[PDB]
Length: 126
Ligand SMILES: CCCc1ccc(S(N)(=O)=O)cc1
Image (cartoon, rainbow, N blue to C red; front, top):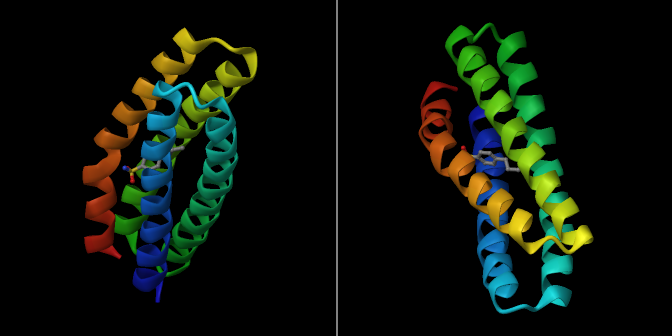
């Protein structure tokens, strides 16, 4: 069901949460070889989450679940803000700009610790 597909997408999101926090620790410790691998892992995880979210949105639209569509449209937009910041963080790493990496990292935590409520609402709407 769309609801179980969202829980699957939810767990995939939690996987990025865990990998991000161990990446943050590695960055602080200066373990750039670890950071690089974690950033690659995160890119895969964020791509996967987005693909699952698109499928769920398309399914809610086919189902005519107007409230779920509204929430998912808002959530997908928020996801994209996160992704743009993530990609900027990756570029900061390639460039060796630790000051921008720190900024982008802290912005991305704010984007995710703000969209949490909406993510929980969607579970209850589908
Ligand atoms: C690239 C990060 C995109 C992103 C992932 C997860 C959430 S949350 N805490 O489920 O609202 C928001 C943005």
